[PDB]
Amino acid sequence: RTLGKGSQPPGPVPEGLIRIYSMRFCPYSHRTRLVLKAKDIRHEVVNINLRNKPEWYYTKHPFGHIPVLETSQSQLIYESVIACEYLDDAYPGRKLFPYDPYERARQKMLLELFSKVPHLTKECLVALRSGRESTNLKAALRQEFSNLEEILEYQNTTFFGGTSISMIDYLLWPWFERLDVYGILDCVSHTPALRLWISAMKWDPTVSALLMDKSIFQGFLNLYFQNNPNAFD
Amino acid sequence: DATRTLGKGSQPPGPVPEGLIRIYSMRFCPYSHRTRLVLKAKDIRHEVVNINLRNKPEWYYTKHPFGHIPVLETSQSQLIYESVIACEYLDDAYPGRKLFPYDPYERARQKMLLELFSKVPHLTKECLVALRSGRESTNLKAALRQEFSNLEEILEYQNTTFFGGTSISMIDYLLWPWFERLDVYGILDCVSHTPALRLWISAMKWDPTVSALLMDKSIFQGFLNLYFQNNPNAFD
Ligand SMILES: [Cl-]
Ligand SMILES: [Cl-]
Image (cartoon, rainbow over all chains, first blue to last red; front, side):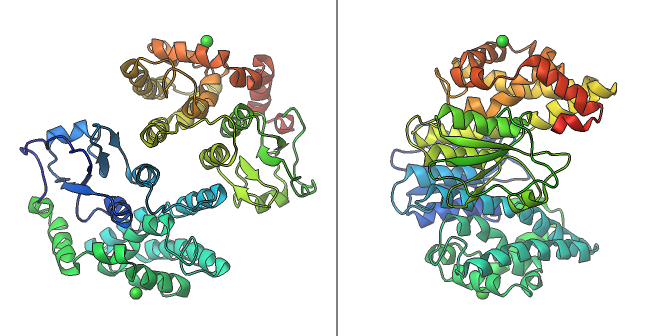
């Protein structure tokens, strides 16, 4: 249940735990939650009301952004990519980034290639939900997906880092999970390797464990676009 | 890196020799300067190939899709870009002196400080362009001063000379090129309210790696004059 304006600050993070400040429908926070689960890290999730934030939350992030990690030593780490990096380095078990410094750099280069997708998927949703023109936004998204399709086809591997899932896949996933409910699943109709990747991801135990309830997510979006503040509670 | 640039019509470089790494650069590019600092700090054996940015070699788009610098090219034909990813790759791939902290939190904190710096490169460029063209600069300078105030707060809170503690580290080298340029850009006045930052500037100038790559002010002044005069020799 989300904490907002009026909520008491949480206590210190206990030794042996790490805390993530999140919101159940935030795709950036979804990234970091995937990495936490995939590495079997003991953690607690504190959800934040993004419309009416707790004033104390600005002591966690100066602009009240999520996700933020808080450690038992009162250290704050943000935002999603830096947090995922930290978790992979700080918790030795099941390394998600590659062993090879070049391959790690390549994954970060792939992440840069992906940089327009979050904005484009969001703008697609807003356009479709507001009845505004979406042809250009979908065309732009299809082009970014073609760039990713070319990588998978060239490599001839199911995932972006090889035959097994790795950090880069989890970093991209949240926006692909959302294509269906956003009404833009048709934007991968020209990219068969990407469609295989989507399925491969759904079969991943960590992805499967964190899959959103589609009906609840639709309910959230409906109240969000009604400007109803209760959408964030 | 005091060599002439390769431009349109030039021939592609051959394979990078075993034991070397190649950086595609330009002598006055601050992003490339960042990566050259890391190469020097770690004593990595390397070759610098300067690219004519006004008149780029056709083959250079096989190194970066949009002809950006810097790009690292390895002896295994691998390409790594741009400056932040290249610097991290260098620090992790090469032994000896390590520039990032070993502690995962301290390393993450350095990445967070880099994010805090993200507006400075564009603001410094915009300030230069405004001053050189005689356009409005009050609000651009105020914006830059605010970004510098954020950095000042970090140094004052930590009570350390450098951004990563009491000695120089990766984060300092990542920020340096734009601070080196304040003088010739004509915006040294934008650190007049930030005394910790002014102390840091001096600490950086005293660093052997920084000092080794420090640009001669007169040559840099000449480059900017040629650049704003639209003289093609600026990029030679
Ligand atoms: Cl599927
Ligand atoms: Cl000085």
